[PDB]
Length: 212
Figure 1 (cartoon, helix red, strand yellow):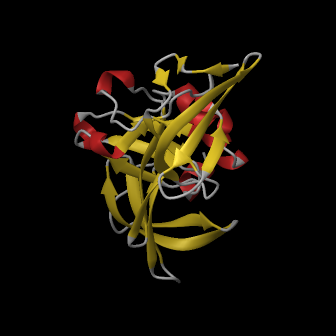
Figure 2 (cartoon, helix red, strand yellow):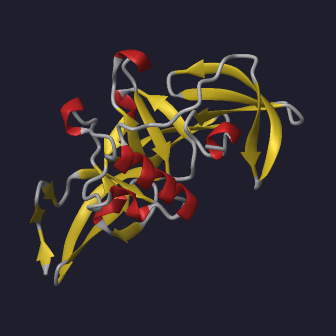
């Protein structure tokens, strides 16, 4: 059937949708379609054509109130890529608190992590019951399932600036150094390549956590 209303969605509303590039973009909800128990959502993008999307591939174009976000919530967040910024899907790993200077910690679908503000987050419209089950990368999906279901039990390595450790990249271990710690994240300098990355302190990419 062709619907005009479905839960709190209404045809003609503004929405964000996932493009095939896996970045998220503004558009208009132009149709809602049913087939049995399934539902699809037709989106016309502002600077593009159309896509027919499942409900976990659309998001509201507003920022959610804090009491509606949990560890495990499925979201779209601001994502820094060189000197460019995108909207990219992720999972909430921490809500605002004193130790993290009142920020949200985001685990993104591709394995990167960052702290963002409430104004940098959007909630996905119809998340899966197990919110991580639409993460395509098996290693990332399995890490987030264990993290979300174990929370608040969070094994982490205690790290200090200057400390020498081994960090994983492309399947092997590299000599690296702790440059900075910010809440549950650490900035790692890869010594041979002289480039830095922010990594979660419970990540199995840190050799002490891999040990365990």
